[PDB]
Length: 43
Length: 50
Image (tube, rainbow over the protein chains, first blue to last red):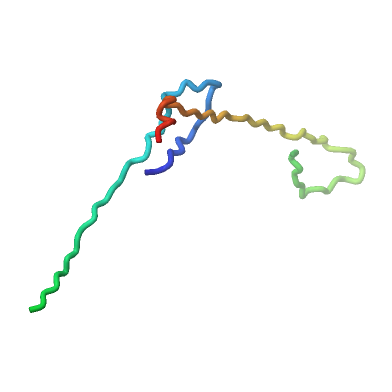
C-alpha cells in the first residue's frame, strides 16, 4: 500500500506512552484470469 | 558578526579630533535541539508467525 506519512512535527517530552503504533499494515490486492478460445472448425 | 557599516561623508576637518566615536558589539544568536522519539509494539506472538 505505502510507507507511513511524515506527520510533520515529531517533538517529544522524554516519554513514549504510545498507542500500539500506527502501523496500519498493507492492503491485500488480487486479480483474476480469463479464458480465450478462438475455436477452429474444418469441414 | 558585527555591523561593519559604510560611510560616504568622510570629509573630516584638519583640526577636528572626533565627532562622537561609534562602536557596537557583535550579535550573539542561540539555537535549540529537538527530540524525535519513535516506538512500535503490537505483541510477542505475531512476530513469530511464518
